Image (cartoon, rainbow, N blue to C red; front, side):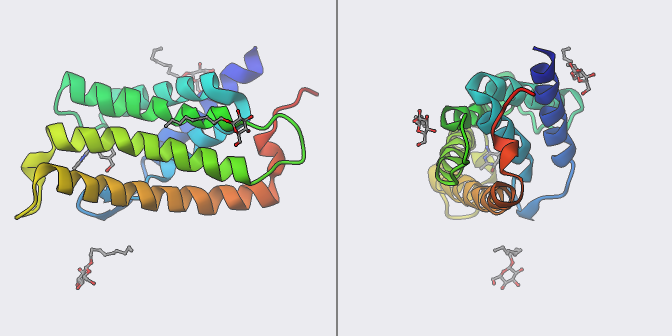
Length: 176
Ligand SMILES: CCCCCCCCCO[C@@H]1O[C@H](CO)[C@@H](O)[C@H](O)[C@H]1O
Ligand SMILES: CCCCCCCCCO[C@@H]1O[C@H](CO)[C@@H](O)[C@H](O)[C@H]1O
Ligand SMILES: CCCCCCCCCO[C@@H]1O[C@H](CO)[C@@H](O)[C@H](O)[C@H]1O
Ligand SMILES: Cc1ncc(Cc2cccc(CO)c2)c(N)n1
């Protein structure tokens, strides 16, 4: 389907275009608002669409050199697997009105948690040389990635709650 392919490409391109915005709170702590179009894609079109949009967004980050890349496996883990994992929100898609808020927040929560889980593992393995003085690798990664995860969920929550209320039909795909 052609409408699908193009929804996917548009939301992935929109994620990258959003990932161009300064979002650093402090050091490597970030508010990852660029996740939002992918989560929106996932919730509206289901898992597969989401994984694919996540995959596309990730490649875009890399090929334009906006990804932080220390190595093949690290970039694999953080710019393929991690953005793809947002598609997990697709398991929470609603196909029939009226749209409930609960599966939107439950899906959003779980998908960001999953992405940041992958960043947390990456922090431990590839990013510890950056840990603040006195901090082991695990504590530092939980701090950076736990906090960033939460702020991201928070922003994702604010924006999708607004969307649920003002434009609920964004989340329900129908023909016609
Ligand atoms: C090809 C392997 C890596 C490159 C990926 C393609 C880069 C362009 C993103 O995809 C394309 O986006 C265009 C703009 O939105 C659309 O014209 C088209 O519908 C869509 O398919
Ligand atoms: C919840 C998101 C808001 C975070 C914005 C903070 C940016 C970096 C941390 O700031 C610091 O905070 C310290 C403790 O308050 C101050 O003593 C210090 O002067 C200030 O540099
Ligand atoms: C860390 C990986 C997490 C994977 C867990 C995902 C399983 C949840 C799927 O259940 C779903 O509940 C939704 C609302 O609760 C409904 O919209 C949907 O129809 C139903 O299928
Ligand atoms: C400790 C630590 N520092 C930096 C990174 C790279 C990275 C890339 C994308 C998103 C995030 C979210 O914090 C982080 C990491 N995974 N762990």
